[PDB]
Image (cartoon, rainbow, N blue to C red):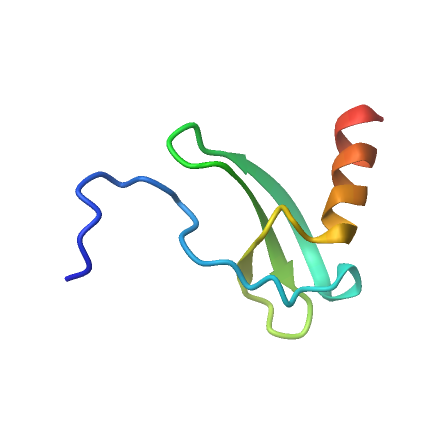
Length: 68
């Protein structure tokens, strides 16, 4: 068992290799015990993946979604 003690982060791993056009659904999770993490559901895979906030299109997404 990989120990974490606490729950820590809902999203542990990030796909990062997720493009805007392959995203069915976007949810932004705010985890105080970790950092920010975005959840996207894949259109082709149909699964939800956790996205890394360092993605450029994500940065674009942030300024759009949080400001407007």
